[PDB]
Structures are given as C-alpha cells and as structure tokens.
Image (cartoon, rainbow, N blue to C red):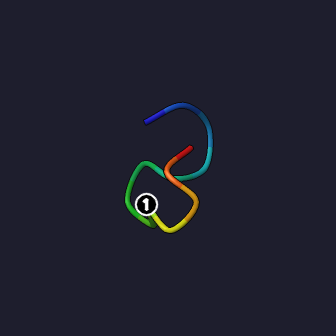
Amino acid sequence: CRRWQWRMKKLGC
C-alpha cells in the first residue's frame, strides 16, 4: 500500500 499497510492494511498506509 505504501510502506507498512501492504499486508496489514489496518491504518490503510
């Protein structure tokens, strides 16, 4: 998604 919420899209990157 950006640099964190790629798999763990909790914050939505």
Quadrant containing the N terminus is top left
Disc 1 residue type?
A: Lys
Residue depicted at x 62% and y 37%: 3
Q: Is residue 5 left or right of residue 3?
A: left
- The x, y position of residue 2, in whole percent, is 54, 31
Kindly identify which residue carries mark 1: 9
- The x, y position of residue 9, in whole percent, is 43, 60
Q: Residues within 10 Å of mark 1 (few under 14, many from 20)?
A: few
- The x, y position of residue 5, in whole percent, is 51, 53
Residue lying at the far top of the rendered structure: 2
Quadrant containing the C terminus is top right
Q: Secondary structure at mark 1?
A: loop
Task: Return the residue nearer the eye: 12 or 5.
Answer: 12
Q: Is residue 6 left or right of residue 4?
A: left
6 vs 9: above or below: above
13 vs 9: above or below: above
Residue depicted at x 42% and y 48%: 6
